[PDB]
Amino acid sequence: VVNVPQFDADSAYLYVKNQVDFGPRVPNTKEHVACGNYLAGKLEAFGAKVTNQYADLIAYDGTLLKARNIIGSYKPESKKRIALFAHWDTRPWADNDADEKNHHTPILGANDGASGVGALLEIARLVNQQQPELGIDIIFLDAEDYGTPQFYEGKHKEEAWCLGSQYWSRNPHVQGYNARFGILLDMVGGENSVFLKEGYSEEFAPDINKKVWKAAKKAGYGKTFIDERGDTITDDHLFINRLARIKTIDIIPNDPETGFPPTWHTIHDNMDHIDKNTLKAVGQTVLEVIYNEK
Ligand SMILES: c1ccc(Cn2ccnc2)cc1
Ligand SMILES: [Zn+2]
Image (tube, rainbow, N blue to C red; front, side):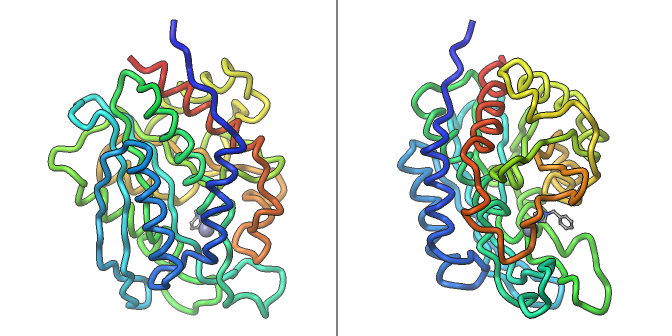
C-alpha cells in the first residue's frame, strides 16, 4: 500500500554527534548560536521551508534567553499537517549528578537534546526524498531545559520549563496554524531505553498514543515501544496540548528503576550512552506513523 522509507541509524547518529561536537548548547552562548545555525541550515539543505522564531524569553530567575525556535516545513501550502517536535537546547547545570561538585556544570545533552533533533533531521532528509501525504513540520524548540535548578531555594514553577514551546504555542510560526496531531521526541537515543505511553499523552491524546504504539508493533519495535502506561511528565507537549490545542504525545523513555535514563542531568549525558539502534526504533516508528496518515 505505502512504501515507508528506511530510517538510516548511522546518518541519525552522526547528526546527534555533530550537535554534541559544538559543546553544550546553553542559551546565550556562541555554541548555542552556532548549533542553531547548523540545524536551520541542515533543514534548508534538506528542502524544508525554514521559519526562525527568535524570542527574548525570561527564565525562572529573570535571565533573558536569546532563544530561537526553528521550524522546517514540508508541503507548506497543505492545510493537513503533522507536527514533529524536539528540544535542541541543553541544560546549563548537571543538577542530578551523583557528585555535588558537578551541579553547576553544563551537560553535553547527547540524549537530552541532541537525540530527538538528530532523529528528526534524518526524518527530514527522507521526507524530502519521498513526501508523505500530509504536510510535515519539523520543529526544534529552544529553552526547554533552563528550568529551576534542583539546588534552588524558592518557588519551583512548572512554567519555568519549556519556554520555547510555550512561546511557539502562543505565537505560531504562521497565522492559523493547524496540525492533525503532534509527536514530541525527548531522549530517544539512550542504550537499552524502552518507551511507555506517557501520562499527559494518555489524557490529551490517547488515540494518538494508540496509533503510535500500534505503528511501532507493526514495524517490529514492539519490544521497544511497550504497550503500558508509564509516568506523567512535564515536557513540551503539555504546553502544546494546553496552549496550541494540538493533540501531541511524548516519546520519552521509562525505566522501572531510574524513571529517566541514568545519564539524565548528569555529566554522563554524552555519546558513550547513545545507541543508534534506539534512534532507529524511534525514527522508524515515526516514519511508519507519518507515512500511513492519509
Ligand atoms: C521536570 C522538568 C522537566 C522534565 C522533562 N525533561 C526532558 C528533558 N529534560 C527534562 C522532567 C521533570
Ligand atoms: Zn533535561
